[PDB]
Image (cartoon, coloured by chain):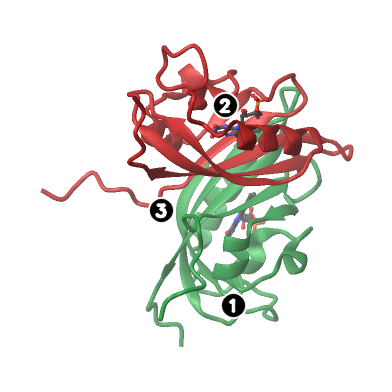
Chain colours: A red, B green
């Protein structure tokens, strides 16, 4: 009873297209797939904010994610700068995760931001959701 | 007493320009800087292979780096796919690290690959070096 171990440190990557509108996800590693429960077909082409919604079925972002941080992310993207912050997020199966997220934008060959990398650190949280 | 901790999990990664010749480094995160000993300005614009020479002065790759694995890396970068292996690397203070390495190419708005994401997982190793 000691198996199916990971061979590398679990790091969670997601990359988006900064040219096409609204930063669609173009890649996710299988650690994101493993922690959030979302396989990659489900999320490819969508925008990450679906993580702020509790469950695949939830229509609206959950009350409890700090709308002030969500706005910092927005501000940071629109200025093409790094973002660093913590916010609530939800697995497919509803579980809550505090996500320490870092967003670094990547430049293309014309002094323009063509992609954005997001590194997720998903911490378990005992938050009460009601 | 305990402090100076880091707030996220230590994930090491770099991004290279896949358009410009020979995959120059355009981004390193600070985990890379902190595990390898090389600072961002020392490595920006250079190719990652300096990690296979032992130290910042050696200009030739170290004998015990597996020439076969380096070759497979070359094949995958060329074939436009993902590499996934383990490869002897060296900190700038000379110490050996088994670098469990993953290369993941990223397509631009185009059908061409414009960037590669490299995720290092450095491991301590008592490999005898002479
Ligand atoms: C590369 C990248 C990764 C992101 N990852 C997450 C994430 O993991 N969790 C999250 O809640 N938001 C993430 N976001 C941000 C959301 O898309 C965010 O809500 C949006 O960028 C700004 O807020 P808005 O939808 O209200 O405009 C990410 C953004 C980018 C560009
Ligand atoms: C994005 C990226 C990251 C890389 N990171 C490393 C690394 O950490 N250690 C290493 O030995 N090689 C790394 N490499 C491999 C070298 O840069 C190079 O592609 C490889 O050594 C094969 O080419 P060469 O035989 O011309 O040296 C990386 C390559 C890329 C594209």
Q: Position of residue B92 (x, y in %)?
A: 61, 77
Q: Is B69 drawn above or below residue B43 in the view shown?
A: above
Q: Nearer the viewer, residue B39 or B5?
A: B5
Report the residue at 77% width, 66% height from top.
B41
Question: Within 8 Å of ligand 1, the CB of disc 2?
Answer: yes
Question: From the viewer's perspective, is residue A86 above or below residue A91?
Answer: below
Can residue A117 be seen in this snapshot? yes
Q: Which residue is mark 1?
A: B54
Q: Residues within 10 Å of mark 2 (few under 14, many from 20)?
A: some
Side (left or right) of B27 relative to B12: right
Query: What's the CA distance linking mark 2 and mark 3?
Result: 23 Å
Give the chain of mark 1.
Answer: B
What residue is pinned by disc 2?
A: A48
The kind of secondary structure element at disc 1 is loop
From this view, report whether residue B35 is shown above or below residue A92: below
Where residue A83 appears, x then y in whole percent?
Answer: 67, 44
Q: CA distance from mark 2 to mark 1?
A: 41 Å
Residue A60: x and y in percent read 51, 15
- In the image, taking residue A67 as reference, residue A126 lies left or right, namely left
* A20 relative to A71, above or below: above
Q: Is A47 on the left-hand or right-hand side of B121? A: right
Image quadrant assignment for residue A78: top right
Q: Nearer the viewer, residue B114 or A27?
A: A27
């Amino acid at each position: 009873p000691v198996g199916n171990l990971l061979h590398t440190a679990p790091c969670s990557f997601v990359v988006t297209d900064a040219v096409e509108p609204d930063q669609p996800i173009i890649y996710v590693n299988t650690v994101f797939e493993m922690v959030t429960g979302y396989r990659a077909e489900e999320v490819l082409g969508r925008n990450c904010r679906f993580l702020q919604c509790r469950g695949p079925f939830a229509k609206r972002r959950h009350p409890l994610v700090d709308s002030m941080v969500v706005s910092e992310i927005r501000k940071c993207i629109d200025e093409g700068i790094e973002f660093q912050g913590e916010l609530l997020n939800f697995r497919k199966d509803g579980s809550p995760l505090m996500n320490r997220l870092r967003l670094t934008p990547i430049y293309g060959d014309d002094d323009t931001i063509t992609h954005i990398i997001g590194i997720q650190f998903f911490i378990e949280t005992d938050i009460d959701l009601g």
